[PDB]
Amino acid sequence: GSSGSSGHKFTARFFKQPTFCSHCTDFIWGIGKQGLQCQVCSFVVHRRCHEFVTFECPGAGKGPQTDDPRNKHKFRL
Ligand SMILES: [Zn+2]
Ligand SMILES: [Zn+2]
C-alpha cells in the first residue's frame, strides 16, 4: 500500500443515524457501512470519497485561515 494519507483523520465509526456525505451529495446509511468522520472538521465522507476529498482540513495540518467560521454569539439561554 502507498504510505501517505495526507488527508483528514478519517476513521471507521458506527453511525446509529443516517449520515449524509457532504462531498458527493449522496446517502451513506444503506449502501453499506462506508463512513469515515473526521475528528477535526466533523467532515464525514464515504470510504471512496475520502481519497477523492481535495479540501484542506481547517484543523489537520494548517491552522485557521484568514476567514472565520464562528458567527454572532447567542444572548438568551
Ligand atoms: Zn460521498
Ligand atoms: Zn477534517
Image (spheres, rainbow, N blue to C red):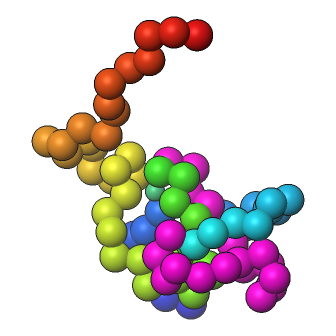
The quadrant holding residue 12 is: bottom right
- Residue occupying the point 76% across, 66% down: 18
Q: Quadrant of the N terminus?
A: bottom right
Whether residue 76 appears in this view of the structure is yes
Find residue 48 and report its horizontal and vertical position in percent: 57, 87
- Residue occupying the point 80% across, 60% down: 17
Find residue 53 and report its horizontal and vertical position in percent: 42, 77
Please determine whether, in this image, residue 52 is positioned above or below residue 12: below
Main structural element of the magenta stretch: helix, strand or loop? loop
Residue 7 relative to residue 77: left or right:
left
- Magenta stretch bounds: 22-40
Please determine whether, in this image, residue 12 is positioned above or below residue 2: above
Q: Is residue 23 magenta?
A: yes
Q: Is residue 20 magenta?
A: no
Find residue 51 and report its horizontal and vertical position in percent: 48, 82
Q: Quadrant of the C terminus?
A: top right
**Total numbered labels:** 0
Find residue 75 and report its horizontal and vertical position in percent: 44, 10
- Residue occupying the point 71% across, 78% down: 28
Q: Nearer the viewer, residue 52 or 4?
A: 52
The residue at the far left in this view is 66
The quadrant holding residue 68 is: top left
Please determine whether, in this image, residue 37 is positioned above or below residue 29: above
Residue 36 relative to residue 70: left or right:
right
Whether residue 10 appears in this view of the structure is no
- Residue occupying the point 34% across, 76% down: 54
The residue at the far right in this view is 16
Q: Nearer the viewer, residue 47 or 18?
A: 18
The residue at the far top in this view is 76
Residue 35 relative to residue 8: left or right:
right
Please determine whether, in this image, residue 15 is positioned above or below residue 52: above
